[PDB]
Amino acid sequence: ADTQGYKWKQLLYNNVTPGSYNPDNMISTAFAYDAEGEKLFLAVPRKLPRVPYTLAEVDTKNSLGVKGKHSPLLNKFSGHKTGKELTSIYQPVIDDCRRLWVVDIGSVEYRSRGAKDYPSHRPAIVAYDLKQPNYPEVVRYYFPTRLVEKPTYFGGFAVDVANPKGDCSETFVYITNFLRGALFIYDHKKQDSWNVTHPTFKAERPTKFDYGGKEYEFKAGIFGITLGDRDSEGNRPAYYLAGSAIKVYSVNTKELKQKGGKLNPELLGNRGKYNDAIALAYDPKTKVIFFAEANTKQVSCWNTQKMPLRMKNTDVVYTSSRFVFGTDISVDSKGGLWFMSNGFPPIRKSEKFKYDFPRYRLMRIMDTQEAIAGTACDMNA
């Protein structure tokens, strides 16, 4: 229940001319922590002008639990020279073998000012090897034109590594898209990809978001996906949720991996009214799914082994009135639970939302077992 982590009023960059960008336009949407390397990676999408590095890193070693170091400066990704190697990303993910994956959207989202600096191209899945320096690029796949379907609305994604104790090439990437309600599946081994849609991906009803004493709304489809325990032969539950929804589902990865196959997802079932979350993360140690919530100012949990999922089978691992809009959550290599808020929900003009307290908040609970102690999510039942 005790946390260490970071707080930024604005995301400032190190080694970038002051005044060359507007700090309030630097809006981070997601992160990934590499525990072995003690590096934090942040996605800053090029949604507004003059973002110097869309993939930023911070070294956490002389930082994490130290007083006075709550606000580290962002740096260029060590795998980059110019910062143009990526156009705009929304989410970084670290896999079982320490490859940092990102989805390059391929274009910026503003006109002029100067968008000309970041030439448009097709969307791409890119991966870097953190085990080597300086993070060489090991995957780079462009989307075939016939498959592009509103790339600006990609959400969370998962990396399915079938052979973690091998060359790690038998890998799938499952990428959410919260507009339509669609999941883009990429087969790394076959160098093929396809689109999948389902009634279960779509939103249930608009989410309520409170800002400045008024109430705002948004209606998001499938937004987060996380992967369970691998069985006998490599297949696994892939738990997903829509952002504007309280139900949770799992479809098997074997149905997912088969191109043009029928999908049979399982409801399991819901988390209680007003508890919409856009991000969720499975902890293999405690078998718990953690949820970073849109409007409740809380991170919540459910033990996958306590069936079925009802509110009564859920609890709270974190509460802060300054935890406005949870946007990313994940478990690291050393079992640490990490969660982020940015006050930036998918609503018109939300980039311009401002807060008295620091907008950007990233926290770690050291180990998940400590987190769920004395909660409905713990081991005793």
Image (cartoon, rainbow, N blue to C red):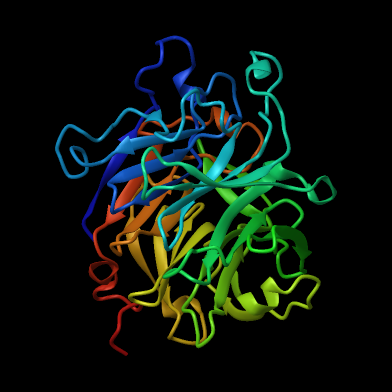
Extreme-front residue of the structure: 167
Q: Is residue 276 visible in this depiction of the protein?
A: no
Quarter residue 283 falls in: bottom left
Vertical arrangement, residue 349 with respect to residue 207, above or below: above
Q: Nearer the viewer, residue 80 or 236?
A: 80
Image coords of residue 189 (percent x, y): 64, 63
Q: Is residue 321 left or right of residue 161?
A: left
Quarter residue 164 falls in: bottom left
Quarter residue 10 falls in: top left
Image coords of residue 95 (percent x, y): 45, 59
Q: Residue at x 56, y 34 (%)?
A: 45
Image coords of residue 296 (percent x, y): 46, 55
Q: Residue at x 44, y 9 (%)?
A: 19
Vertical arrangement, residue 341 with respect to residue 249, above or below: above
The N terminus appears in which quarter of the rendering? Answer: bottom left
Q: Is residue 39 left or right of residue 187?
A: left
Image coords of residue 247 (percent x, y): 60, 71
